[PDB]
Image (tube, rainbow, N blue to C red; front, side, top):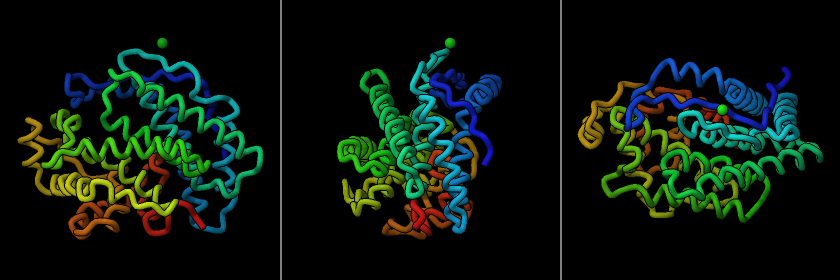
Length: 309
Ligand SMILES: [Cl-]
């Protein structure tokens, strides 16, 4: 259990796309952002590592280590200060993703928490939920996949604290994504991303599936809302990794060649829920899948449950 990075109240991230469709990356800006947000990405990667180690069994120490890191950031007010804006809103996106990583790690390890840790961490996760929700009050912030990802931290906080109000907030975010799917299966804000259209349909599916999976922890089946619409979207993604011709024509660009990885691991859960599960076998074979922003090892969580016994 090494020492945590500092948890500053403040964030200063850098946007890295060159074009109107935010589909081509400037590698100099990407390197600059990577260095600027390194504490946030190292925090998320470590707490997910500790949670995965706890889930193997016979390692309560790894679970307690995650809680030590979360408590330290809670007591320093991490991410609750200034979101600095340089060339876009990357600082706010980073707060959305890192809140998700922290809240997932707490949900997986909270059985081991002390009294003081519970109060410290749950208070911090609720303040982050309120701050992230307030960003979307401005109607000029377009509610694409960043909005769905904001729902990850709100929903994990809701389940862990048993807050029916935050639970209703998250259900609204999930339903807004489901309602955006068109009859032909597209999400229009993601189809606008040219050679990354397929990439961002995959990336928008991931948080919607994860909130639905978290809802099973309170016995609810969110896949009955507009039943079948999420399957049309997921089927287009699986089809697209086989043959991208539909994404090519509807986006106006040839899709960037890529293998499924990281957050593509939503398929590990969803193949257990679909009426046509073997359609997702080709994507499954690219695994195992790990993503700290989704709680860690998705291949193992789909078999063993999100929260270890
Ligand atoms: Cl600045």
